Length: 241
Image 1: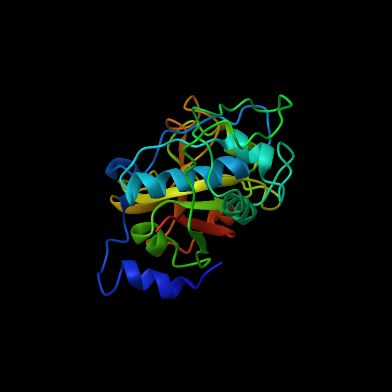
Image 2 (image 1 turned 90 degrees about the vertical axis):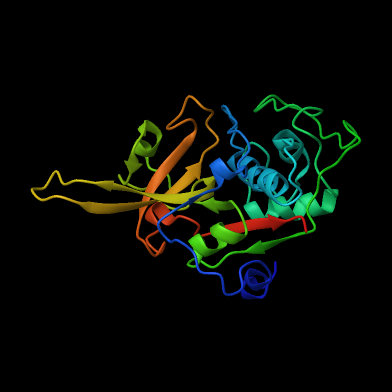
């Protein structure tokens, strides 16, 4: 809901940057991964997560917000039955902030009315930008983690570690967040020596006991244009400033 290039300038400028790697996780920009459990709330978890990061970064504050308040009050979405990232940010603005993870605990699929009053300190967002299907790493590098969508194939769930590059799903069927990229330099199971494998770093919402501490690495190229499984097809990053 804004013009990227217009904002990317206010944060980057002429500063060049390393395209091989930047990890918001270890620079205090990624709050802990959560677990949506058996409720289809990925969208709420993804948007909330990107909001948590803007605070962790910009307003240098660690705060975890209620995905449950979104599942219960974002009407432009369908609670456990699904939703859309931007709709979430939308309703976030409509609601003028979300209660803390703490005053409004998550309860997954268990019926639950929406009570905006369950707290007094609502954390909100001034607005939210949509980042270009490309220029991802760029956004990621200066704006912060990004709520994105992806086609998750069945094997995506088995991912236990490494750099997943397996089969993808049918269509965009999940919201996760991009928190950075990196590049491990492997050798060569195919006869030679060195080689560079670049990857994006995803923060899932299936709890820590999944993939690398809840995070997963998806293949990509130095450029950050190779978006396996539809990565960031839909990509947004909220702004609290």
